[PDB]
Length: 277
Length: 277
Ligand SMILES: CCCCCCCCCCCCCCCCCCCC(=O)O[C@H](COC(=O)CCCCCCCCCCCCCC)COP(=O)(O)OCCN
Ligand SMILES: CCCCCCCCCCCCCCCCCCCC(=O)O[C@H](COC(=O)CCCCCCCCCCCCCC)COP(=O)(O)OCCN
Ligand SMILES: [Fe+3]
Ligand SMILES: [Fe+3]
Image (cartoon, rainbow over all chains, first blue to last red; front, side):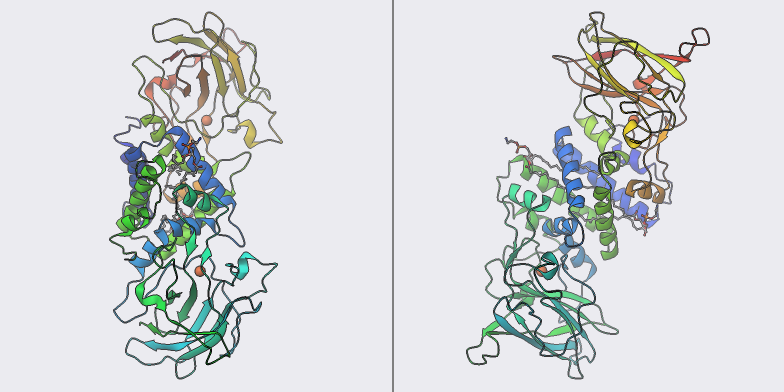
């Protein structure tokens, strides 16, 4: 007949004109099924529906050059981490992926080893070093170590374009024959995700804080290897067990050593990445 | 301790700081549960995730004074009809609700009975008439009949702000003691929902058309009665069995009679509304 509540799912899915084995049909069949199930499960009202419409609208409207509020929504509802988890499984011993987040920027300067990526000098100086190897234990020559962090104010460069220098706490480093990287930066600082839009509103309404534990992002790539999209977390950070975006993994926690002794930098963090074929 | 695929839902929901019985917690618990189930069900890829982010973003960004693309998305996935369905359980004999759609505009001119709502004179003239009553059969005095339709070009006034006169095919009528309404308009025309944004892209990808059968919208309100948000459909419209927004109900299909004899209007359509509660 016409639409009924009991046949809502079949009614909507049955309008599709594409073959059932087309990937879009498989995805959309499940999306509609789950969406209808949700609405029925909690009895979404007309007013609640209107709230949702308004929220989704504002979420897209606040997106633009320096802000991806839909990524933040995905991130804070654990969707991003879940997508990473089911797609980027790897053997024991290989460094684990985690949530990408929205603040990677392609085409960062290719810098020299030992260069200082902290261009505004805000934070405590830190020496970052380690080795890229394959799963069989061999250093990889010509791996690209693409790194990004916030500054001491809790912001990535792209969040404060007219304040932070371009490429602040960003750089790309290409390993030599020994697989080693080394650069100077600052010790990362815990930061709230942008909380002045819908995502911040929702966290507030759920009695959730917006913070992530301090971390340095590493995107490590090499010919013939799976792309490693990860971060290292500052050991001891108070938010390690309450990351707003669910990104922490035990093995990604990095030690930070205080350097009275080597006063080139105040801190050092050593961390080795292991890629798979 | 940390996020795992198999504990993804508990991990995310467990961060809520509000009481389990708070409406936001009930809704969001189910939203996260269903959203994670969906992602797992069909194995959303990183690329698919990225496509969704972009799509949701564009959907919100194209919203504005004259277009609610999130409503259209809700409508075309059957969510709007479903929310209307589960929030109404009216008695036998009361006129049924259906999908609101995005084109109602508050504060339409209060017109006299017999006034013509068709200001651009595009379409075949039609006389619309009927009676508002209660379930016991008594006319309702002082009901407001708030009506809106497209013009012959298949657009609501707000979709062509520089072309259509303001309030074209819109008006509010207040019933007298006999409960009767009467106005002149045009016979409505089948129309595609706006198909140049994400929603149109999606329908195209699913091999679905963007069309609705011809209809006149009626929002009927009265003191002490449930708000009636409905439409009447043009009998015999070839899209009655394939409404893009699933809004058709048998009882809302209206008969249209041709008037050779009184060529004041070409057509007349008589339809009574029965309010409840
Ligand atoms: C294509 C389909 C599109 C439509 C699909 C429908 C989806 C429905 C799911 C969302 C429904 C959630 C809303 C539940 C409302 C009740 C509890 C939460 C908020 C609530 O209390 O509502 C209001 C306040 O909310 C606030 O101030 C903050 C709430 C923020 C908005 C609600 C959450 C948005 C939904 C998240 C997006 C969906 C995820 C994307 C995949 C006012 O009520 P009150 O009781 O506080 O007032 C009394 C004070 N005097
Ligand atoms: C919290 C945020 C969550 C973040 C998102 C994660 C959730 C996963 C959602 C995944 C949806 C992807 C499904 C699309 C199928 C793609 C695979 C088929 C092959 C292909 O490339 O087709 C594209 C289809 O994508 C398209 O048509 C573009 C994608 C459109 C799908 C998005 C619909 C989402 C519904 C939102 C409801 C709100 C829920 C609130 C609780 C072509 O591209 P094309 O078709 O454009 O080109 C043609 C113009 N006809
Ligand atoms: Fe980050
Ligand atoms: Fe309409």
